[PDB]
Image 1: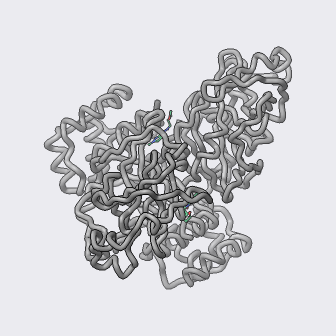
Image 2: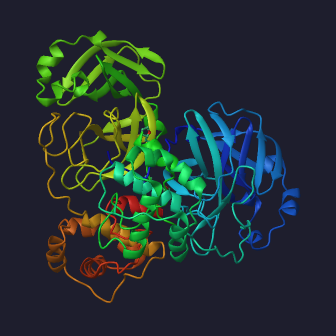
Image 3: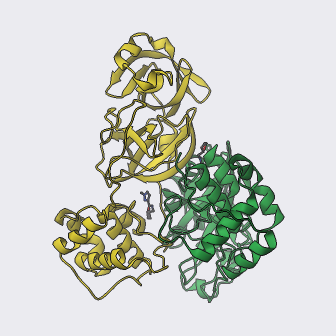
Length: 301
Length: 301
Ligand SMILES: Cn1ccc(C(=O)NC[C@@H]2CCCO2)n1
Ligand SMILES: Cn1ccc(C(=O)NC[C@@H]2CCCO2)n1
């Protein structure tokens, strides 16, 4: 029993983290096979970051200007290319610790683990969600760029995020491992406001199922609702619309608990309308939305 | 910026996890040098667990009855002993992945990372605190016993917890790596009620400092208090008494923010007395107490 915000064990990713220095900028790189992936803004001075022309900045850079250090050993850079907002540094040595891996682009509401790193050194691991506004609410200090987000499926690491920047509101933006930003964000120190941080409804319902499985049942009520009725309430409370796809994904949790998805929606509706009245659910005084239905099944199984 | 519940990177501990089977019971073991540490209740049938005599049960066990598997490779058990509530299985092979390590017995209010494992396989990592009632609020299913709690200091793993059991209230009890339970708990399936789960006041204040550092300041007020006045309020709200030792430990956070510890106590006093009024602090609607002053400095530095 018990339900915790749980990250994937980070060992397979720790084995991939390196330090990348270009001129005076140091950040983190991901070393898979004989390629090191890092944010292209490694080539920028903080001055450059105001209006960088990355193609023009990169012309002034040679392989030997990219210093790549794996622990206390230097890697030899034999090639470099820019793909979207990441640099790919070809090194002469395949990472011997390369895990089975994929690059995936996640959808908003999907959760992943972050391995926060500084100077190529793993410093902590926490669980994130891609927010509906394509930001993440991370914990990143200067030097953390190039830290990565990932899921693990048995022995296969799916990398989904590389950290690039902090918005003035202190939320985080980054890319997939093809270097495409999540959302509208750019690797430029400019006005970039995030949109509405809506609640990931399907995740909240997953977590209410987790609560029932773990003995927290006070919020279960005598009501049901419909998707359309529930969605009127969701809209009013800046919750994501619930779709039949979401209902289908919650089917196994519905089955396990014997609570129909629409009955749980009606519980969630009353919680939105009435609040918690000073009560808690799985040790939270707010409705948690950074567990996916898959996360709840995983943790509960 | 941003403040997350962060675990230590788990790689160094993943390298130590093994499967231990005795008869029909499988749980996890910790392999350091040529010793495998595991809960002694590995030798119990679920029937045994009602009133086990461990010395008598252990007489019926030989080295060859302890099956120790590290990945898909069997370790040869050449000795076994019971130390308090753990078994030490001597194997013929030193764990080649043994990190620098210590065994530490933590105090209530101290935080640590748990690597939840099943069949010797790391399944997730989360951050815990030793509660003032010597329980932890974990996430452990059947098969998770022998999962461990740890802190990391650069390259040295301090192991502080091994998981042994779940109380009927769904909170968790375990030992240090010398096999001494935290608190009054025993490895017997009997009536074991936890005492008052009081709030770790010094941790709450640490986290309020973290909030200020990260731009969440709405709860700062015009008041101060004294340790004695604050402690009258703490007692009323089932908070741990704050000592001058706690004030001294918060000194660096006080210095960094320029908020006197007793001023932050007066903020905390108003939050206890007034509640959050539907507001949040670092994304929480309750006062978080599973960050130590050391955790806040670490994450903020
Ligand atoms: C997102 N994430 C990573 C790990 C977990 C998790 O819940 N692990 C525990 C489960 C219990 C049984 C096997 O692993 N969730
Ligand atoms: C308990 N714990 C484990 C890890 C952390 C943590 O906050 N790591 C991030 C820091 C930022 C700078 C270097 O590591 N806390």
